[PDB]
View 1: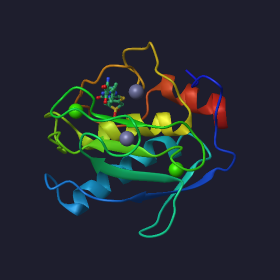
View 2: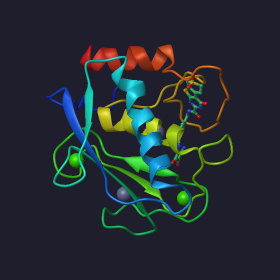
View 3: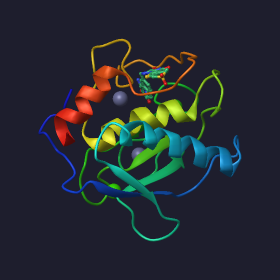
Length: 163
Ligand SMILES: Nc1c(N2CCc3ccc(CNC(=O)c4nc5sc6c(c5c(=O)[nH]4)CCS(=O)(=O)C6)cc3C2)c(=O)c1=O
Ligand SMILES: [Ca+2]
Ligand SMILES: [Ca+2]
Ligand SMILES: [Zn+2]
Ligand SMILES: [Zn+2]
C-alpha cells in the first residue's frame, strides 16, 4: 500500500495552506472539511498538521479548472475529482481539487471531506488499496456512518511508513 519508490516525508510536523476556496461551500465549511480530513491520519500516526494562511507550506491545497500548470489537467464535471503528488519538496505533497465539481458536506456527490482525506493519503506516500472498505480503495462511494474514523487497512498503511 506504499507508493512506488517508498517516498516519505523526513519530518513529522507538516504545514498546509488552503490557497483558494469553492463558491459551493462557505469558507468555514471548507476549512472544517480539510481539518477533519487531516485529523483522520493524525490520530493514527505521529504526523502533526499545522495550518498557515500565508507563506510556503508543505502541502498546498487549491481548487483548479482544466489546465492549471502541472501538466495534469482536470476535465469538467465528474471523472477525475482531484489528485495529489507524492512526498517531496516543491509541488510534492500538494493536493488539487477540480473546481467544476459539485462539492458538498453531505452524502451527495461529491463530499469534500472524503475526497480530501483520500488525496492526503497520496500526499503522505500511500498507494491504492485493494480492500473495498479502505479510504485508499480506488473507487469513490460515500457511506453514512455513526462514527467517522480511518479504516484498519489505512491505519496499517500509515503506520508501516511513519509508525
Ligand atoms: N478514482 C478517482 C478519484 N477518487 C478520488 C477521491 C476518492 C476518495 C475515496 C475513494 C475510496 N474510498 C471511499 O470511497 C470511501 N472511503 C471511506 S473510509 C471511511 C468511510 C469511507 C467512505 O465512505 N468512502 C466512511 C465511514 S468512516 O468511519 O469515516 C471510514 C476513492 C477516491 C478516488 C479521482 O479523483 C479519480 O479519477
Ligand atoms: Ca473532473
Ligand atoms: Ca509541497
Ligand atoms: Zn494539479
Ligand atoms: Zn487515489
